[PDB]
Every structure is written in C-alpha cells, then in structure tokens.
Amino acid sequence: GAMGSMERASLIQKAKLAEQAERYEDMAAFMKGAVEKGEELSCEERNLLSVAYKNVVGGQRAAWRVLSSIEQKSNEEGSEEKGPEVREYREKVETELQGVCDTVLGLLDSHLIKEAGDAESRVFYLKMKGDYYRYLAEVATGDDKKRIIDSARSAYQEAMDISKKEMPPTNPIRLGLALNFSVFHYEIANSPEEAISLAKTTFDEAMADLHTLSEDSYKDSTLIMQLLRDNLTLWT
Amino acid sequence: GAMGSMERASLIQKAKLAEQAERYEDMAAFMKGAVEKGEELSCEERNLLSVAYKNVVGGQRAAWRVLSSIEQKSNEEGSEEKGPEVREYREKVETELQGVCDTVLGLLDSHLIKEAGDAESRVFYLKMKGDYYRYLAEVATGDDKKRIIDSARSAYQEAMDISKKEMPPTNPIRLGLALNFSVFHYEIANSPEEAISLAKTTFDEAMADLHTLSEDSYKDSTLIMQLLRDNLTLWT
Amino acid sequence: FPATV
Amino acid sequence: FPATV
Ligand SMILES: *CC(=O)NCC1CCN(C(=O)[C@]2(Oc3ccccc3)CC[C@H](N)CC2)CC1
Ligand SMILES: *CC(=O)NCC1CCN(C(=O)[C@]2(Oc3ccccc3)CC[C@H](N)CC2)CC1
Ligand SMILES: [Mg+2]
Ligand SMILES: [Mg+2]
Ligand SMILES: [Mg+2]
Ligand SMILES: [Mg+2]
Ligand SMILES: [Mg+2]
Ligand SMILES: [Mg+2]
Image 1 (cartoon, rainbow over the protein chains, first blue to last red):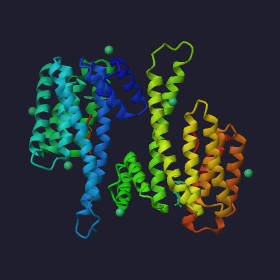
Image 2 (image 1 turned 90 degrees about the vertical axis):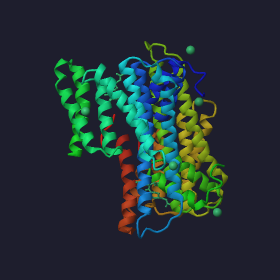
Image 3 (image 1 turned 180 degrees about the vertical axis):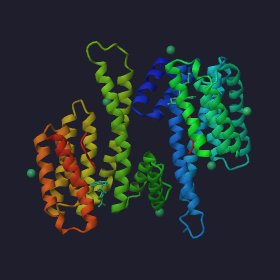
C-alpha cells in the first residue's frame, strides 16, 4: 500500500541502496512494493527479494532462539518465578516473525508462483515457500504444526521434482534447494537419515557435473557444495 | 503511549531481555515507556536507556554515512544522472534519525534532567543531551545548524562544569563525557586543538588518580582512558 | 545450526 | 571514526 506511489524502478533502486546500507527492513519493504506492481521479477530482482526477507527473518529467528532458551531455563526445577514477561516477549517476537513469514507467503501466492513458468523462477519461488513454512514450523506448537510442516514439505518436493527434470545437478538454485530441504528433514521432520542421504547424493551428482562448467559457474556451484559438506560433517 | 498499560518493572525486565536478544529498537521502546512512568531512573536503568538508543541511532548514523557517500559520488563530474532516489532515501533515513534524536531529547527535557539532582545522574543526562544534539549536528545543513551545534556545546559544557566540581577525575561518566566532548570539538566544532587538549588533560588527570582506586574501578576507568589515547593517536 | 541459503 | 561512549 505504502509503496503504491513509487515507480517500480525506483523501488528496485532503493532496495539496492538499502542493501548497501544494511537496512534490510527497508529493503524488504521496497521489494514488497516492487512485487505488488504485478510484473514478474527478473533473476536479479528475485535475489533482492530473497536477500531482504532472509535477513529480516534471520534476525527474528536468532532473537526468538535467545528468548526461547531463556524461557525454557525459567521452566526448569529450582528456577525462581519471574512472572509472565519472558513468555510475553517471546510471543511478541514470535508474532512478528509469523507476520513476516505470512507476508512472504502472501507475495508468493499473490501472484509470484502462478506466473512463474520458467524452471529457474518457479523452483526459486517454491524453495522460498518451503523456507518460510519451515520458519513457521520452527515456532509452531499447536493443532496446525503438522499441516505447517506438510506445507513446507510439499513446496520443497514440487521444487525438487522440477529442478531434477529441468536443471543440471550443479545449478545453484537446485543445490540451494537441496541444502535447505535436507535441513528441513534434519531439523523439522525428524528424518536425519533422509537429510544425510539428500545432502550426499546432491553433492556427489554435482561433483560429477563440474567438468561441464566455466570457471565462474564452478565457483558458484562449489560454494554451495561446500555447505552441503559442512552439514554432512556436522551430522556424521 | 503504547507502553502505558505495562508495569514499570515489566518494561525494565523486557528491556533487559531485548538487550540479550540484540533487539535494540524494542529495548529503546521499553525504556521510553519506563521513563514515561515519571519516576527517576536508577543507575542501572539510565544505562539501559543509553545503551538502547545508542545502538538504534548508531545503526541509523552508519546507514546515513553510507547513503551520504553514495550521494556525494553522484554529484561528482562525470557521474551519470540516476534521478532523485539516492537523495530521497538518504532523506528518509535522515528523517528517521532526527526523529530518534528528538525522542531522546524529549525524554531528557520531559522530565529527566530537571529531576536529576545528584551529580552522577545530572551529568549522565546532560552528556546524553550533548550527544543527541551532536547527532543532529552531523546531518544538519540549514539555517539552524549553528544553533544545533551550540545546543550540543552548552549541554556538554554544563555537564563538564558539574563533573569537574563533583566527581573524581577517574569517574567513568566524567571520562566518557570528556571523550565525547573532545570528539564534538574535533568533528563538529572544527576545533581539533581543543579536542586534543581536552583528551590529553583528561587522560593525564585520570592517570594521576588511579592510585586511589580498587581493582574493579581501575578496570572501568582505564578502559575509557584507552579510548582517549586511541583518539589522540588518530589525531596526532 | 546447519547451513541454509 | 573516533571513539565515543
Ligand atoms: C535468479 C537466480 O539465478 N538466482 C540464483 C542465484 C545463485 C547464486 N546465489 C547464491 O549462491 C546464494 O543464494 C541462493 C539463494 C537460493 C538458492 C541458492 C543460492 C547467494 C550468495 C551466497 N554466497 C550463496 C547462496 C544467489 C542466487
Ligand atoms: C549509572 C552509572 O554510573 N553509569 C555509568 C557507567 C560507567 C561504566 N560504563 C561504561 O564505561 C560504558 O558506557 C558509558 C556511558 C556513559 C559514560 C561513560 C561510559 C559502557 C561499557 C563500555 N565498555 C565503556 C563505556 C557504563 C556506564
Ligand atoms: Mg510506472
Ligand atoms: Mg504464539
Ligand atoms: Mg532420493
Ligand atoms: Mg505500577
Ligand atoms: Mg533533511
Ligand atoms: Mg581547559
């Protein structure tokens, strides 16, 4: 709404300035405005959108984890009663986090995904959908936790199916999707074996296709392959 | 307004949680609410207030400097015209920064300063007043720049006069005041000689009084003395 | 915490 | 930038 009077190109320009200034909330608001113009996003623009919201929600998740840890300690035997404040403030942060996730999911549903026909765009958006449901799942404790988890799984699975058919095994989007879906398995779905298998198979199939790549594509793919290895090392 | 329904003690508790979570905007809002209860602040509470706003405005200042640098580069010969966006976004950040400064100054004026009778509280608040006028001065370019600068100077000078009469030369508040007033001289008032003299005299008078201190007071005072030395080294 | 992108 | 507290 607030960005309705600003030109699309000016919103994109400002998102880039906001990134340089490390003003990620501003960057996300600019990119939301740009999406709401209704035109499809280019590759560069999709990456601006993802960076902005990743940084905003990343900060909320880190804060939530600090507060949840304090709250869990408060519920241990021998802890002194300090009143409702820790729970209240964790809830406040949580609600704000959920709001950001709902905003992103809303942009994807209205109407980024449905207009995305090329494999690279569609997989990118479906990965995002999986990621923001995963963030919702991290904080979910009630009747809908299972459905939230399944929503993440379904989005990731659709993305995986497209990526395997349409993209090479070194494609950075396909690699990043696999990295994150593997973490979903380990941290959310209580499926560490699936997580490890996915990471390993993804790494090995990428390794086998590196020979096809330019120097610059090699750099991009090997970076994410190293993240897969890092997780495998953490988990084995 | 928004914090009017929350207990003072709960606001203080939450400010501390927000600090642990690195949620400095929340921390500042909680502390604003606490001030607006109308009771004087304890030493610990004054420090919570200062930390919160220092971190919020510190981030705005860093962003402002990034954007101002981009804007200055845009105004160099041979730079391509990119439209009003850089100036607009610098102005947006600037206005937000000014707003935070005005909020802090407002808390000090209504009614922290007037109720602060003890030297340690009064000097602390007057230092803050000088600091937030200094932040206003950093971004000021119009008819009132001189008056803003003079407002900073006057606040710092009152604080200096009280601190010299009422506090030992090692007192951390007195040291921090001197450190910041010295930076005011160097960066705002175009008085590098005054800045250097102040820093040197402050350091040397503190050095001479260290012998009176406990181990823990020595640690506190020497930390800020090292900042004075660091600035002297930068400037000489 | 594991790596995601 | 110089140190302030
Ligand atoms: C439009 C498009 O092709 N986007 C994909 C880019 C591929 C390279 N990128 C990355 O490697 C990082 O972010 C990712 C987001 C989603 C999927 C995979 C990667 C950004 C730089 C980091 N050092 C590594 C991940 C940007 C997106
Ligand atoms: C109520 C009171 O006595 N406050 C003064 C504290 C003295 C010790 N402090 C500091 O040294 C730091 O912050 C300052 C703010 C204002 C004046 C001087 C210091 C906080 C820790 C940093 N490592 C050094 C500065 C806290 C305030
Ligand atoms: Mg237009
Ligand atoms: Mg909740
Ligand atoms: Mg398989
Ligand atoms: Mg009360
Ligand atoms: Mg202005
Ligand atoms: Mg003198």
